[PDB]
Length: 155
Ligand SMILES: [Mg+2]
Image 1 (tube, rainbow, N blue to C red):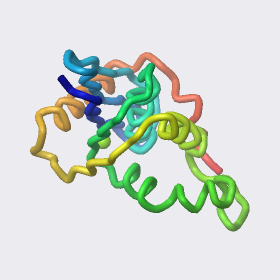
Image 2 (image 1 turned 90 degrees about the vertical axis):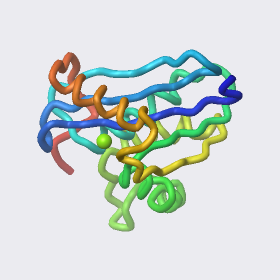
Image 3 (image 1 turned 60 degrees about the vertical axis):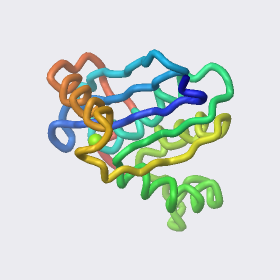
Image 4 (image 1 turned 180 degrees about the vertical axis):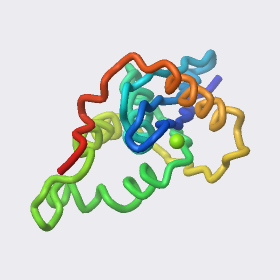
């Protein structure tokens, strides 16, 4: 039994911005539950995070989670950039909100009622899933049902 869940994540977004898609699995105790959906026009960043969310967002009890991911947005955001935000209010020193704060403030919910270990894979060609996840994003790309309302094209 996955005696406390391993999560996999990715996200593609076909242009910048163009339609995006999030890839993900949660292998809950043993079984596996997956997550996908298309965004009419979005970005790579907001799809990785997006993903980092959902996964957490549907974990009903107090899990011990291994969120393995590839990202250098979600890594760079965790092991570096957040620590300063909470410290300042999610504002630059310019005292100008940060980009994507909308999804950022979120992942930070879910990432505060669970024990998370980040397994930042280069991986590429590692754990079927890191790739599975990928497929899943390319797949939701090609069929975009929703509208990324957080994605504000500016400021
Ligand atoms: Mg990606």
